[PDB]
């Protein structure tokens, strides 16, 4: 009916008193980027803020912080009417009080630390009935605006005086705490959190409206991932941010009871969550309650498993109960708990990527006060293999080193703690450096599924190869309708071949980057491990990982490794199919066409490969990648030298011109040797200057300077003497003969 | 829209059912002025005011399950009706015959194929008293409360004869004996055995059970008098999946572009529960596209608001792109769709296959009178790509038989990971679905993987072809299971296969000739919109020494060039259009709708021969030295 009615969306701008709107809605309401609006909510309560603009905002929604959201008695998905208020009134006296559960460690002064940089250069519109949150001093604290003279709302001016005296009071019985978990505390898994919201938010926010449809909801969700990836966090945050009654079941708490007290507690859990519909039951550590049937010895464990199965079947006669569970891997669960009607939906919460790890480090360092040199982006780029609990432990351990550097001014004030003393505490980059040097991550053995960062500009030349890979990978994704109309089955695999070091892994990562797909890489030793220790279920688990993360590029490096390890041209006997490429063939034949999983293999020895792979339908395209030519090597050297500070070269084109018959690895070797010579000379100069300085004490001219800041032509002219060709001309002759005898042509014009 | 253009004869005492708006609703004709019956005219007025009333105590509900809710398994449902309907509808008339009825039926299949549905529908549509036993509900009780519940179940179903006892998930109650550790589980198994023997002294009680595979049951429950009859409910075919999608979309209201036949043709590996989840998930996407007019009417729901809800084809497209089926690893037993017109030429081969496969089925009396044992196997051989799998599927289509296909990697998996019970399970699947054609592709794969002409040592029989020979020798003649093998290397095959009684007929399939390649190209190009060719016969004439795979490669490369040009034209026209904004002549047209001769003339440059002349020489020499003749007229 009215265009000011809006629905609440998430917060992006991390200021408390800032709401956001889209561009055509603000142009429809005729606002400005410095205005002051008012929001009406439930329970006859309102909130005053400052409206700004946002381009990523949707059409009929509003973006606001959790503080403003909780001050309106509003949850995600409610309705809010907005109105303009030009009544710009400056305040006179502001009387606020702290809350006792958030001040139970601090005492003395609060005005200079918390509030003095809070209102300065802010002009925050406050109102009687608001609770705001101040972070800082390794502590988050909640204040309530108790009394203002311009009732109800006023903009805080420098004319105002703030009487922060008084006793701390308790919480109102209905005011929820900002200590508990919302969507803001979760980082790095935006897609899985959005998927869980799409599954669960509609049968909870609209129970009776969904009851009258005729659509069955989901009734069991199975979260899985490595330990420490925050599954209990996600369950509790989806619980609290929807108002659903959340009951917790802990695995060892039930399995630690007696023989007859476990089933009674399960029955009490499900019967108690009946009466508070809509409810959420979270069964934590489902591996403890119901493991595999062979791992259950006894009768009590099997009675507990059968009791859980009976209750999960009894949910179908119930109404508005969602059951979530969390494991560490799928294959440790009794497979009767995975059929239809019992945990049919599965969500995978993997280890984070670099953007994810940066978001984790920004979440855990809200309250802590960093120094000026601390750059969290380099720390996030350095941590590899760390799950979120490792990053929390890293932040806490660096903060403890920063405390244990100075135990001089800390200890003498023993009875009370003032906030200025902890404001003297500031964490430096050396703290995070030592915390990186001490910590050991837990997910190093896990496989990495992430989008690559290599672009096309790291690769020199090979233009028709780029065109052919864009034809094969990208056109069935962007334009499916053309393949539907012309009636063509799209091809599914590509085999690269060529000399070693010529950039096949870089092309695979670049085409995974151009389509914004995931990338799973499988080396040669991971195939030889399956060869020696005879194990073939791992090949099925690989294609399962590839299907759960579609669209993706699955890259098999060194397919010729087993056929080379078994023998040369003549193996043990009859160099046909082996054990592992057989399972690869069966899984390729069992591949669905709708998933868009694209398989790339790579070899160096195209003649000893199994010929059953190159049959149409498995890997039919062959691409030959040659040694780079005279124009490519410049783009090779510029891509390699982009981090080392080179300077004052005469002719880099001559450097690429003189090297003929060199792969990319040889040019990388030349650049690394030049960097070696530069580091050696720049350490020798520092040692010699320090020795000559200390030999004549009290040096009169202390004028600091860097002797070798950049790499000069002497280093390259020395390092080129150690250059070598990796590929002989007989090998190039063999690849050229395979490329000639591979190609046959008619060349005759039919018309 | 119910009475409009209907002229429905109604009567006082009728209850009718109206579907629509994602809901089925039942109305009762309470009062009419032309008593008892009248045809509804446009002159009529319908007073639909009043309060809703309850149900009469004897009026059964149309919410419960009948035969209409089951799709895709018409044959198995007919077989269960033939087994069960006569001892239920006529109890005392069957009592006075002297024929024993069945007394235990075992349904099995993959999870999600609707076995509880079939049991409940056969229960309700015969009026039999239906008692349900659930496996975990009994195994979740105490030590002494399980056997009392089993005894109460059988004793209570005594008093309401005729009755049906359905034991759901029999794998939970009575597993294999080695998987039972303890004494309580063995007492439950022995109690069930004692009651199933006690049924023989009882009257008019049928016991049904449902498993997930036969081999997880204690084998004492399969002997005579205890679950002797077994019914297999497999995964559905395309007609079956279309019938499932039509059943689950009764109440939902589809849009105009939604074609369920393409959705049924696309879903492969989906059991019926996957199709129900697909329909529900697409309907939830159609709701979550518009949460604008839905939310503002919060207290009540009007049916017109859900009539604005209409599910489009993009909803089913996304639901296909998100869903993952559960029966991809299972073997597919179905009738093929390839006919004889997809294959070019080979006429005497078609005649010989019709003599071998079809004549012992259509005319058994001629083989009885003349006194001939029919042959049982055929071995095709020839160059690769010459259409052996197509001939196997075509002869399975002509006789309307099932088709089980076994590739080369499924034999090499049995070779490397040494396992031979799977060969017996294959012939069991082939006998339970007779008449069928069982096709072994690439019999030479193990003898090629073990070595060339010289293996490891002594290239005689291996491990897996040995089990194939024992199962062929153990084959009954009445079942009509027909076995076809296929090779490319006829000289390294085990000679013990070609002995009379196992695979005695040999057929050589050559490279296709000048007339066949036209029928190859027409069969390949029948989906791609080609146009305005000059001489397709010249296209088939110039290509000499080309198998079917090479011609398929030529057609696929022509389609590649066409798709590339038709994307380049759209990109270039959009760039030139956006470069000069507010384009004054917006006249839409397709640049390349059809494939022209330029694409074929470009793609023929990349053509190649797959088979050399030495290989053709070797197959011709094997065909010559295979054949010996007397050629002498005895009379
Ligand atoms: N994605 C994340 N975002 C923010 N904090 C996280 C994240 N993952 C983990 N943490 C932190 O690490 C703690 C550990 O999370 P948990 O919920 O215990 O993980 P977990 O999956 O439950 O591990 P297990 O298997 O139950 S021992 C959380 O309480 C957070 O403090
Ligand atoms: N052939 C079918 N026709 C119609 N609906 C079907 C069919 N098969 C399955 N369904 C639907 O899917 C649901 C699942 O059927 P079930 O009886 O649970 O299958 P099931 O064999 O019992 O699986 P398990 O092994 O017991 S978990 C049914 O209630 C129907 O809604
Ligand atoms: N064409 C190229 N352009 C740029 N760098 C290259 C090129 N070829 C190889 N390199 C560099 O040399 C190495 C090549 O690695 P990779 O492509 O995996 O080699 P290979 O294909 O022999 O397995 C990497 O250090 C890479 O950066
Ligand atoms: N005689 C034929 N006529 C038409 N197409 C054929 C013929 N033989 C093979 N093909 C084509 O090649 C493929 C079938 O090859 P197939 O006969 O299964 O090969 P193989 O005998 O090596 O197993 C399909 O693309 C099919 O259309
Ligand atoms: Mg946990
Ligand atoms: Mg069932």
Image (spheres, coloured by chain):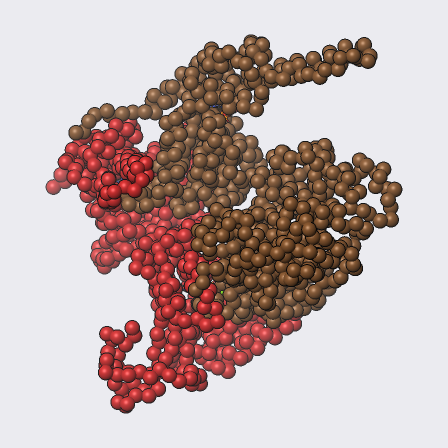
Chain colours: A brown, B red
Left of A720 or right of it: where is B21?
A: left
User: Where does residue B557 sit, x and y in percent of width and height?
Assistant: 29, 35
Residue A436, by quadrant, is top right
Residue in view at x 56 percent, y 16 percent: A647
The image shows residue B146, relative to residue A366, as above or below, that is below
Please say whether residue B244 is visible from this viewpoint.
Answer: yes
The quarter of the rendered structure image containing the C terminus of chain A is top left
The quarter of the rendered structure image containing the N terminus of chain A is bottom left
Left of B431 or right of it: where is A307?
A: right
Q: Nearer the viewer, residue B221 or A452?
A: A452
The image shows residue A483, relative to residue B137, as above or below, that is above
The image shows residue A605, relative to residue A41, as above or below, that is above
Residue in view at x 61 percent, y 48 percent: A15
For the image shown, how many numbered marks are present on the structure?
A: 0
Please say whether residue B219 is visible from this viewpoint.
Answer: no
Residue in view at x 46 percent, y 53 percent: A30
The image shows residue B491, relative to residue A77, as above or below, that is above
Q: Nearer the viewer, residue A184 or A7?
A: A7
Residue in view at x 59 percent, y 15 percent: A711
Q: Nearer the viewer, residue B255 or A441?
A: B255
Residue A69, by quadrant, is bottom right
User: Where does residue B512 sit, x and y in percent of width and height?
Assistant: 22, 36
User: Where does residue B601 sit, x and y in percent of width and height?
Assistant: 22, 31
Q: Nearer the viewer, residue B626 or B607?
A: B607
User: Where does residue B122 sit, x and y in percent of width and height?
Assistant: 41, 72
């Amino acid at each position: 009916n009215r265009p000011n009615r809006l629905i609440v969306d998430e917060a992006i701008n991390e200021d408390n008193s800032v709401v956001s709107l889209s561009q055509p809605k603000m142009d429809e309401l005729q606002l400005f980027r410095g205005d002051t609006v008012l929001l009406k909510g439930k329970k006859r309560r309102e909130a005053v803020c400052i409206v700004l603009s946002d381009d990523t905002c949707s059409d009929e929604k509003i973006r606001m912080n959790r503080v403003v959201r909780n001050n309106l008695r509003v949850r995600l998905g409610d309705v809010i009417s907005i109105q303009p208020c030009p009544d710009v009134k400056y305040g006179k006296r502001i009387h606020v009080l702290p809350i006792d559960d958030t001040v139970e460690g601090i005492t003395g002064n609060l005005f200079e630390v918390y509030l003095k940089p809070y209102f300065l250069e802010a002009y925050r519109p406050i109102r009687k009935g608001d609770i705001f949150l101040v972070r800082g001093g390794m502590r988050a604290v909640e204040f309530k605006v108790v009394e203002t003279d311009p009732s109800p709302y006023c903009i805080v001016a420098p004319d105002t005086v703030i009487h922060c005296e008084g006793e701390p009071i308790k919480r109102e019985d209905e005011e929820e705490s900002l200590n508990e978990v919302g969507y803001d505390d979760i980082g790095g898994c935006r897609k899985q959190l959005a998927q869980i919201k799409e599954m669960v938010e509609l049968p909870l926010r609209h129970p009776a409206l969904f009851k009258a449809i005729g659509v069955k909801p989901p009734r069991g969700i199975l979260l899985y991932g490595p330990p420490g990836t925050g599954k209990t966090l996600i369950a509790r945050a989806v619980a609290n941010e929807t108002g659903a009654f959340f009951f917790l079941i802990n695995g060892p708490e039930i399995m630690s009871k007696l023989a007859g007290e476990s089933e009674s507690n399960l029955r009490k859990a499900f019967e108690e969550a009946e009466k508070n519909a809509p409810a959420i039951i979270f069964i934590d550590e489902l591996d403890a309650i119901a493991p595999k049937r062979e791992k259950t010895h006894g009768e009590v464990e099997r009675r507990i498993v059968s009791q859980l199965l009976t209750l999960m079947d009894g949910l179908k006669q119930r109404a508005h109960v969602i059951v979530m569970a969390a494991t560490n891997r799928p294959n440790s669960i009794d497979p009767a708990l995975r059929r239809f009607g019992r945990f049919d939906r599965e969500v995978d919460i993997g280890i984070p990527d670099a953007t994810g790890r940066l978001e984790i480090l920004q979440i855990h360092t809200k309250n802590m006060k960093l120094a000026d040199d601390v750059d969290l982006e380099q720390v996030a780029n350095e941590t590899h293999g760390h799950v979120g609990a490792d990053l929390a432990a890293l932040c806490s351990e660096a903060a403890l080193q920063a405390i244990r550097k100075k135990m001089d001014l800390i200890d003498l004030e023993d009875e009370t703690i003032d906030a200025e003393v902890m404001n003297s505490l500031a964490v430096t980059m050396d703290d995070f450096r030592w915390a990186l040097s001490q910590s050991n991550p837990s997910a190093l053995r896990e496989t990495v599924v992430e989008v690559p960062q290599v672009t096309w500009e790291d690769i020199g030349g090979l233009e028709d190869v780029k065109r052919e890979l864009q034809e094969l990978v990208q056109y069935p994704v962007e334009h499916p309708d053309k393949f539907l109309k012309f009636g063509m089955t799209p091809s599914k695999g590509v085999l690269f071949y060529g000399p070693p070091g010529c950039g096949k892994t870089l092309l695979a990562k670049a085409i995974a980057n151009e389509c914004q797909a995931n990338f799973i890489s499988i080396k040669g030793p991971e195939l030889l491990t399956m060869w020696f220790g005879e194990s073939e279920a791992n090949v099925r688990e690989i294609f399962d990982k590839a299907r759960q993360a579609a669209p993706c590029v699955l890259f098999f490096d060194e397919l010729d490794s087993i056929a080379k390890a078994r023998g040369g041209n003549i193996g043990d006997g009859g160099g046909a199919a082996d054990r592992v490429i057989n399972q690869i063939l069966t899984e390729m034949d069992g591949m669905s066409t709708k998933k868009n999983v694209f398989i790339i293999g790579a070899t160096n020895r195209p003649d000893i490969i199994d010929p059953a792979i190159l049959r149409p339908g498995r890997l039919d395209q062959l691409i030959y990648i040659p040694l780079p030519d005279e124009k490519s090597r410049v783009a090779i050297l510029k891509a390699n030298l982009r981090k080392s500070p080179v300077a004052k070269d005469v002719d880099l084109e001559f450097l690429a011109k003189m090297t003929n018959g060199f792969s990319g690895a040889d040019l990388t070797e030349i650049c690394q040797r030049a960097c070696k010579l530069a580091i050696r000379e720049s350490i020798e100069s520092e040692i010699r200057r320090e020795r000559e300085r200390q030999t004549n004490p009290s040096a009169m001219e202390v004028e600091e300077d860097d002797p070798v800041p950049e790499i000069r032509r002497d280093h390259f002219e020395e390092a080129m003497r150690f250059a070598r060709r990796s590929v002989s001309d007989n090998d190039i002759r063999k690849y050229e003969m395979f490329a000639q005898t591979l190609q046959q042509s008619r060349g005759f014009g039919s018309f």
